[PDB]
Image (cartoon, rainbow, N blue to C red):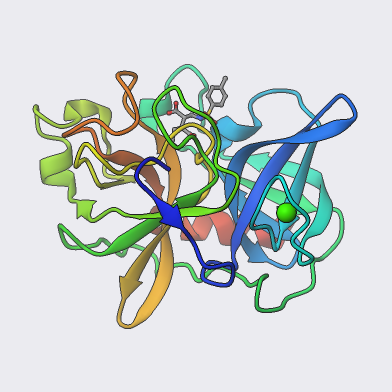
Length: 240
Ligand SMILES: *C(=O)[C@@H](CC)[C@@H](CNS(=O)(=O)c1ccc(C)cc1)C(=O)O
Ligand SMILES: [Ca+2]
């Protein structure tokens, strides 16, 4: 997250860290949202490589023991069947991870509330991106979880020629684009939390930023629109 602030450690209890095995240790690669005690929602592009993955829930600082973490292996990976690694702009950048063990819920570990199917936010709706992604374009991951206020940019504006044009689809949510705050590499997969009727709900799964950089004016961070995939998510959890 570029231009973020450090989140309080119990603000976003559904945020998870998706990590891969690297030698004798583990490395953060993406975020995710805990949606059941044994299921995580993340981006399909985060699980494209043939790596060994684990999920960390109750995480705040990646480089320090917080005394709240729970570590669980990924038992099954279900990518949307229409995802294509050669075309992130086509959409379908979503995947569900079945955890080997069910995690225990507490003030640091909670299920993410998902919007009702079909819900579209009005332009400029209040949202926060959260993650441990780079803190600057071509920078380094954050140690502590970060958050940034990214108001939505509706489809009409976001798919206009000066923004993302035809690259953005109506199955996506755009947010931000101010040139200062944005998602960045390593935030992908994680949540876009938006305040609706008093309650924050996870409306987006971080998917991409401009190839020019993370915080680029008129290139808002782009997310998979969760509310387009409610039936798909329910169908996967029910058949697995
Ligand atoms: C996600 O973080 C996204 C920017 C918000 C990235 C794409 N995903 S990533 O950094 O996790 C990634 C990059 C390259 C590879 C080979 C794998 C994963 C983006 O650049 O849009
Ligand atoms: Ca930690």
